[PDB]
Image (cartoon, rainbow, N blue to C red; front, side, top):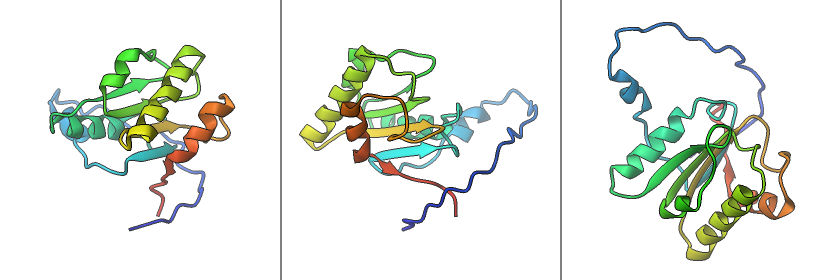
Length: 149
């Protein structure tokens, strides 16, 4: 249920302070629920936080299934990513060439098999980001979800 998303550009404040009991509760803050197969978010999560991405990766890992999250602005993409069934990519925009074609191939392997779980987050939009048209068309297979009421 939902199907409602309207671009309300607010929440530009970090809002954080020292906890700071040094608990392992940081893992509990990660532990969330799963969601749709192909989900693209912008703002509410994909802003260099990726905690919901890590949650989604972890809940898949618990099922004995392969899952990984990659910072597209901190870590490079590898062919090893094809081992994972659940992929999460945050800060997608800085994709260059090989990694972008690799990602494209990932999209194909997903759509071809009828499998593949993907979660992307950034600050703009999939059809507005500076990417090649071959990848951009594949970005349309991912849903756009805003957690805004």
